[PDB]
Length: 82
RNA sequence: UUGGCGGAAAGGCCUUGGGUGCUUGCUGGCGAAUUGCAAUGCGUGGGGAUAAAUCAUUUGUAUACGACUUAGA
Image (cartoon, rainbow, N blue to C red; front, side, top):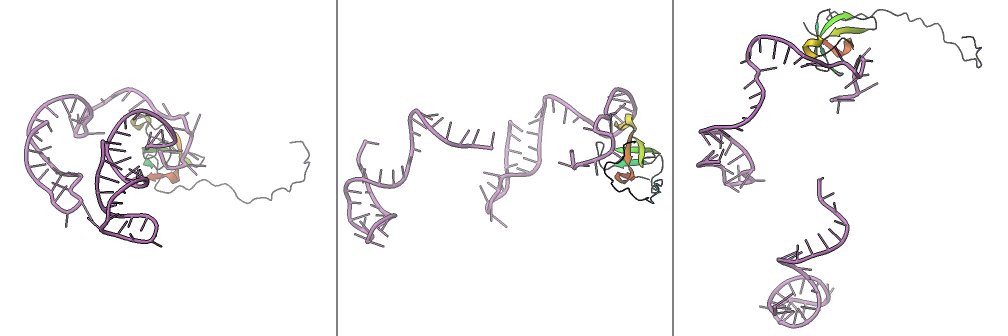
């Protein structure tokens, strides 16, 4: 914060990479039934509830039906049913 | 547990009878969580008894040396 650099490491250039919201595939819609391909609950059927700002999908089993609680999941490890 | 069957490398096929579990065929309840967003998720090396082999002896229907051929608790 206030310590002067004791070794003049070169500063990084102005990176021209602005963050953009994830463009999820149209097949992913809220309320869709999802199949988990990996992780603790791999192979379980899950319901798509909400999209999170961290590029993850807020999902629920529901917990009562199959024991899968509210957890974050990646869209790339999920198959969206009709 | 009963009966038959499979010889090509059968060694497998059913099957009468009962025993004990599941049944998602149908109706419901209990728990999943925090692993936190994926890192696939089987015989020795030393002893106790002993079935058998080789050597010793002998044998000669065998013989350059191995090998082969007999018999004595």
